[PDB]
Length: 270
Image (tube, rainbow, N blue to C red):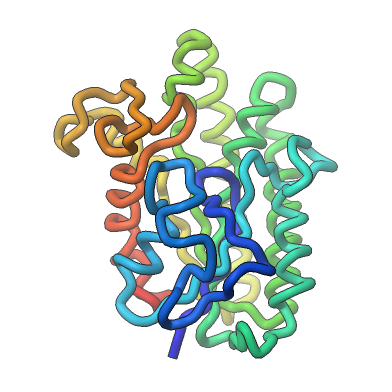
């Protein structure tokens, strides 16, 4: 009795899953590509670890996240595969519960990790207090599409401190600060939206995972996690927090998945 884990997001979540590639099954829970391919981590990412390492029962991963994604190109634009397009792919292929993914309210979990690129592109050109509610409202309206399909279990990850990625550290501390302050407003509004959605619907099971605090703990004390510092980059994915200047490696993603596991028990797969 599988959990169908549909995920949406950006390169922190991408694996290169194609809706026309091999589909998830008990013998192949990621569908495609092989576990540990297609990520920005040199190995599995948090979805691969949640699906195949941290799972308490069978989890089938349908991972629609795409590199560079923003929430909606009508707001902060970037790449064609925005979150809106990921939801459209979901609606076109999986929303009607086909034989390949015959999910139900009791066994589908919809995970969304978005906002890194919206903030990364708009933190200096928009007013966080009045602009981030537009982003969050659009996220909520996409979530409502899945709700109308019958989805009831949702996982939202807040935005991690990409202000402290090497890519942003190099822009100067006042830019790190400007970006971080904007991000804080987004995450606060994200939290408020998840809380309001949960209360308003009354029949949903939701988790807001505070990736920001978790990765901040590691950045603040890297050696306690076996990393030599909080800034080095190594594309082996394990020697440093950072796989490249903007994406953390597989060791970080495994630590996050391990941190997430107990918080996901209520969602059914963990």
